[PDB]
Image (cartoon, rainbow, N blue to C red):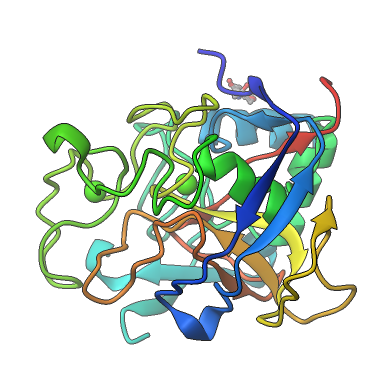
Amino acid sequence: LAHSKMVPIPAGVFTMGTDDPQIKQDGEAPARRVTIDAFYMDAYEVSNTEFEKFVNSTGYLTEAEKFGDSFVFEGMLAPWWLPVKGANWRHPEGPDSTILHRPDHPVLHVSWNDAVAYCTWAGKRLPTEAEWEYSCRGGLHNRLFPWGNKLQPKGQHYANIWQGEFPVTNTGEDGFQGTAPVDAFPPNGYGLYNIVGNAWEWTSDWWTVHHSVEETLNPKGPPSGKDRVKKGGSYMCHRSYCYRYRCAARSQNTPDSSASNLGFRCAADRLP
Ligand SMILES: *[C@@H]1O[C@H](CO)[C@@H](O)[C@H](O)[C@H]1NC(C)=O
Ligand SMILES: [Ca+2]
Ligand SMILES: [Ca+2]
């Protein structure tokens, strides 16, 4: 295992967003050309084991632990999100759940602040939304998914999302009802794993839905806001109610929020 390994994301210009938005309320549009300097991205979502090395070193107590509750999806105990007392990264469905059998799965119940603490501890940082989307797209232009426009290319599952009738029945057809190991599923063109699906991923940007079509260079998002941007979708997503396992998709939460489907990966200017 090399679950803290990074890959070099090459310098380039890409189209961020889409002029064919699918969730218009989320500011997926307009498409805009964005220039990104070469940098490094974690190949994997930060795992339980890797987060435990952080906590072992620093003694860090996560915001969910201090608050004393976190949001858990009802189907694994909106109306299907329940604030559960004693749910946190070590007990992802509440006090009598454990991570001992899933050490290689993504860490969950981590806030934006928790993520920044981890990444900075590791000599890294969160990616910006633009870096994240560029990396997600994996060197392809204007495609829905890291791998192209088909959800199941060659009849193969390429990401851990939902199959079945949400929220009642997850068939587990793709091989995972909850999370999968951080190295599950094929990599995209840049060597990134589970950049769509599995856990949602925090980014550094303040959220807004108002974007210019101006061209930009290493954009950081707006200078203020109340919610931070998260990307990529999770194991809960299904086309029927969600459609957020697209690189262009985007959503938000307050920086002190935490949930059973939300995690992160780090980036860095140079190798730490
Ligand atoms: C964290 O520390 C505990 C107790 O010393 C140890 O048993 C465990 O293996 C450590 N975890 C990691 C991921 O290094
Ligand atoms: Ca699944
Ligand atoms: Ca993910």
